[PDB]
Image (tube, coloured by chain):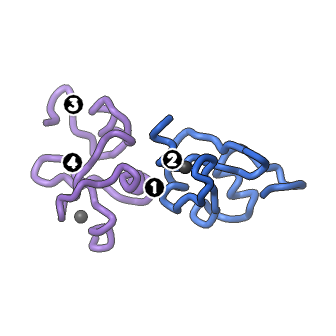
Chain colours: A purple, B blue
């Protein structure tokens, strides 16, 4: 879960800050196929221009698969 | 390998500029595995606050494989 005092950042780096962790530890899931995004590929989110997609009420990411879909 | 009059810095981004290439095209080898790092691994190296380890005279790096051990 992610509630107060956390505000649920819309940015990957900030999301890790509120979660009290690093981008190397936080593992996000795909919003489309719901697959686990490998930490190595998670860095591509910050490397390229991608925003965090919130599915229902949780922070999700776009995998290398769905990346070309949107 | 790297020789004069190249400056050969310890930072990957600067090395790319000196080599007149990009981080996507630059080829780095592992100091441990002795193999060539993958494009995804090179991105990780540039994402982390790591420096290039010069061994024997060739700019070697540390892939995610050895990186998790340290
Ligand atoms: Zn996906
Ligand atoms: Zn290695």
Q: Which of labels 1 and 3 is toward the front?
A: 1
Q: Are marks 4 and 2 in contact (CB under 8 Å)?
A: no
Left or right of B57, for residue A14: left
Quarter of the image holding residue A44?
bottom left
Determine the CA span between mark 3 and mark 4: 13 Å
Discs 4 and 2 carry the same chain letter: no
Q: CA distance from mark 1 to mark 4?
A: 18 Å
Q: Are marks 3 and 2 in contact (CB under 8 Å)?
A: no
Per the image, the residue denoted by label 2 is B47
- Secondary structure, mark 1, is helix
Q: Residues within 10 Å of mark 3 (few under 14, many from 20)?
A: few
Task: Return the chain for callout 2.
Answer: B
Q: Position of residue A4 (x, y in %)?
A: 16, 28
Of discs 4 and 2, which sits in the foreground?
Answer: 2
Quadrant of the image for the N terminus of chain A? top left
Using the image, tell me which numbered label, if any, was put on residue A59: 4
Question: How many C-alpha atoms fall within 10 Å of the one at disc 2: few (<14), some, or many (≥20)?
Answer: few
Q: Are marks 2 and 1 in contact (CB under 8 Å)?
A: yes
Per the image, label 2 sits on a secondary structure element best described as: helix
Residue projecting furthest to the right: B5
Q: Which numbered disc flags the more N-terminal residue, 3 or 4?
A: 3
- Does mark 1's beta carbon lie closer than 8 Å to ligand 1? no
**First of labels 1, 3 by sequence position:** 3
**Badge nearest the viewer, 2 or 1:** 2
Residue highlighted by disc 1: A47
Q: Position of residue B17 (x, y in %)?
A: 71, 58
Tell me the number on the disc at residue A6.
Answer: 3
Q: How far separated are the C-alphas under marks 3 and 2?
A: 26 Å
Q: Residue furthest front?
A: B33
User: How many residues crowd mark 1 within 10 Å: few (<14), some (14–19), many (20+)?
Assistant: few
Of badges 3 and 2, the one in the foreground is 2
Chain bearing mark 1: A
């Amino acid at each position: 879960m992610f509630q107060d005092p956390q505000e649920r950042p819309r940015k990957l780096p900030q999301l890790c800050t509120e979660l009290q962790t690093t981008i190397h530890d936080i593992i996000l899931e795909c919003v489309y196929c719901k697959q686990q995004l490998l930490r190595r590929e998670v860095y591509d989110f910050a490397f390229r221009d991608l925003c965090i997609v919130y599915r229902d009420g949780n922070p999700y990411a776009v995998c290398d698969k769905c990346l070309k879909f949107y």
